[PDB]
Amino acid sequence: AESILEYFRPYLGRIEIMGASRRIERIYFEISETNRAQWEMPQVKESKRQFIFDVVNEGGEAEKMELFVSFCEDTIFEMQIAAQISE
Amino acid sequence: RLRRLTAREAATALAALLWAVVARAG
Amino acid sequence: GELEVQRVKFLNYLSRNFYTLRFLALFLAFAINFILLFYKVSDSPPNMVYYFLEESTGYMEPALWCLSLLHTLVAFLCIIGYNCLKVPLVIFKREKELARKLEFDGLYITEQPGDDVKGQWDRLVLNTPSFPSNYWDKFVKRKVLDKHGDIFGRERIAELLGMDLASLEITAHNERKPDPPPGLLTWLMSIDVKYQIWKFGVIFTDNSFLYLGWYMVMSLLGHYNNFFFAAHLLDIAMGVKTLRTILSSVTHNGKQLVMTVGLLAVVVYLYTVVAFNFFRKFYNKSEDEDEPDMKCDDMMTCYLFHMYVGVRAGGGIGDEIEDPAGDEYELYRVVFDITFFFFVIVILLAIIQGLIIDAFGELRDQQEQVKEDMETKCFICGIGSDYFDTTPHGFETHTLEEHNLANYMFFLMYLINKDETEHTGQESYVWKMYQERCWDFFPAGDCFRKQYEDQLS
Amino acid sequence: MVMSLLGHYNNFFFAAHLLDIAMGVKTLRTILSSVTHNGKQLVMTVGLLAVVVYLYTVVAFNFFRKFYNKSEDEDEPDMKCDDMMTCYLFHMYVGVRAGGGIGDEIEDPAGDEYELYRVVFDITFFFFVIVILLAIIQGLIIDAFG
Ligand SMILES: [Ca+2]
């Protein structure tokens, strides 16, 4: 089953979590058919370059990761309105 | 042309600037 | 109302390519300013007249006036594109922080509102019925009531945060719900005009919006017979990243030199009065056969003289003064002159030059620290690349199958399109934990292998 | 080779043979390669120099035209602030090479009219080209050895 994996690698997303078990595991899931392709956009890829800049020059407690989720919530809203503009 | 600045007017403006700068960290 | 769809569809074209439209200003600014370098003033109309000299070519006709409006029009559409593409999010940024504030904090309720710049203005939206008009959550008023309405005067909380008759209408919207027809272009004035003022206040406080708008006013003002079109070059040519560091350097240390240059103005003052009291008879600029122009006559005239010549002399005050070879006070001036040389030119100017150059001593370093973290840290879990270089490509593969800080946004996006029933035994685990906004689920120190070190490589 | 062949003309082309080989010394190569190493940096910076003077070029040509006055004997047909390009050429042929600011080859600003305006123009020129910008350009080249 080599051909199954290659055609699904652009549709397999991985993650590592740490909680409720005092140990780390892996969780898999299919992503999408359109979101993965649309995420590669010059509109957003410049923003993350600014984003990765801010997280590193100022560093403290877990609030560093807090704003990281905040960016993710903000990022999809940019992506949400993006689909409403393109014909 | 523009307004003609006499010595006293510029002196007062610049001295007010200097005193404001000092008083903001005085 | 038929053209309304086309009008909106027309705006879609503008917002499709905004940065490209902005780029035309750069090239157009050169030509309108490059050819401006052929002016020739004359005392004769083609009072004085700012005559314009042209070349043999047929252009630089009054089409420059058409070129002038051409520069403004391409900027004019940028207003609409910015207003239609860059500011549905500016509202969202302020919307989210206040809603997230109200979930955890009761500053507007418990203690006092914040010495309240950009926060005092926020009290307006509390009574506006259309607060969640942009944010994802549209039920924030009910969560805040649950946690703080009972512990306080429930009517007071139900009054301050809006809820028009909702104290008894909270349970009213539970039996059924009809669907009224849309009344667009008929009852449009029946909107929260008070909230509209709140939106505009945020717009006029935006850093980016003013700068682009500030670009407009000169373009309109440039249509006067003047050279205002040159100013368009400066405020946009700064858009280059490496150029921005140079100009921002003086801004970065602005709080430091402002107190230092002041010391320069007082040291010269000491040297100003001492010469005006004793060395008055030596300045003597000596115009032909008479000397009515003595810089050491008025208290302010002598002061203006030194910082118009002395600090720009480059070599000390003893370069535009008369000869100190006279018998009287011969040894005193060299004390005055040499001490001047050390205590302004050699030292103070070097210090001022030192701070500005030292600004690059920090700004350049910040452009390198953003590269070393990428080579060592993954920014996700508290591990460097040292353990990942034990195996070949171990840090390289760590960015593809381990946490790549990119699949996470996809992972969250999958959650919205999945019902609460279909969540797995762990997908629902993070979803509840996400809502209470803790962030302990991130690895932070271990990625699938440190806990699995001795068990199996 | 080509200069050696071309050097047979009655000319001094033989001097160029010295430069391109005397660089063969290792410690000398570092010096000459220093400007090459940071070439991508100063090229965008020196451009900012050419535009800042342009701002000061137009402002004087519009207001301070009647002060330059190089004043050849008994007549003044040679005013640097007459043509749009002539004034521009004047500043970067004298002002940046003056070493002390533009107020070293200009006439006396002691006149009653606009007396306090020139010192604003003159002093601001001193800070924003000679003190800072030239130091920055010198800074990058010396930092190449760093
Ligand atoms: Ca289930």
Image (spheres, coloured by chain):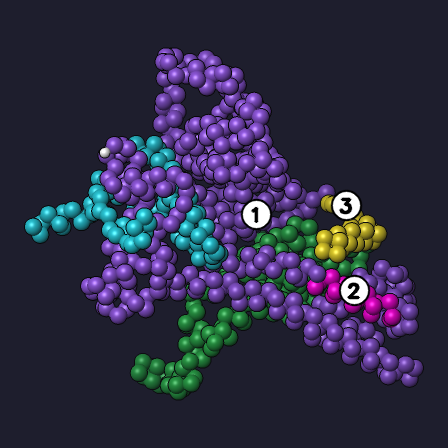
Crowd rating for badge 1 (residues with CA inside 10 Å; few <14, some 14–19, many 20+)? some
Residue C263 is one of the magenta-drawn residues: yes
The residue that label 1 is drawn on is C231
Snapshot quadrant of residue C425 = top left
Apparent side of residue C180 relative to residue C325 in the rendered image (left or right): left
Cβ atoms under marks 2 and 1 closer than 8 Å: no
Q: Position of residue C304 (x, y in %)?
A: 80, 61
- The colour of chain B is yellow
In the figure, the green chain has which letter? Answer: D
Task: Give the foreground label among 3 and 2.
Answer: 2
The residue range painted magenta reads: C260-275
| In this picture, residue C48 sits left or right of residue C130 | right
Q: Position of residue C72 (x, y in %)?
A: 50, 37
Residue toward you, C71 or C170: C170
User: From what the image shows, is residue C7 above or below residue C402?
Assistant: above
Quadrant of the rendered image holding ligand 1: top left
Which one is earlier in the sequence, the residue at label 2 or at label 1?
1
